[PDB]
Figure (cartoon, rainbow, N blue to C red):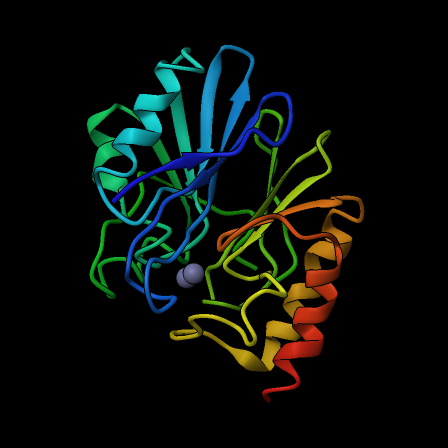
Length: 220
Ligand SMILES: [Zn+2]
Ligand SMILES: [Zn+2]
């Protein structure tokens, strides 16, 4: 139901937001709140439609300036989940073109403009100060990773994950046969992002990247 913020760089806030959906009890999910001059921008929305309202609320209350846009890492209820709020707050949603199709084909909303130049599996567009990067199929075929160039922040998302939870999390509608290839993608798509944020508890280091491909092969 709720929402937490861990300032983890100048310009940049982390979004936590807890529900008892996946990780047994209360689980975590992450987007980031990025600030682009006066503009304000977000990778990914919480679990629900009210958890992305409070992302917006604690933003005017403590960041201030107005949101323009919100990029969704993929067509999964943790990553879309909240959308309708973005729409109602005249926010431009930007799903990657393979997302806007697995959305209403797996119980959810499709983002406004569709992101591309990244449909075909080791690509990137640009974005103000932000970098959308596609790494192939992994956690879902449309999972999408982002770094803010000058913060050594990467966001692999539901793709890269914490050494904390034993295995790899929800791996439903996806491809294991590329995953381990695709965790690499970023390690070298942003060779520098020391601050790898991930969408289930605190940013580890550049070692989850590596361990995940190690891991996805422990269970393969
Ligand atoms: Zn997911
Ligand atoms: Zn997830």
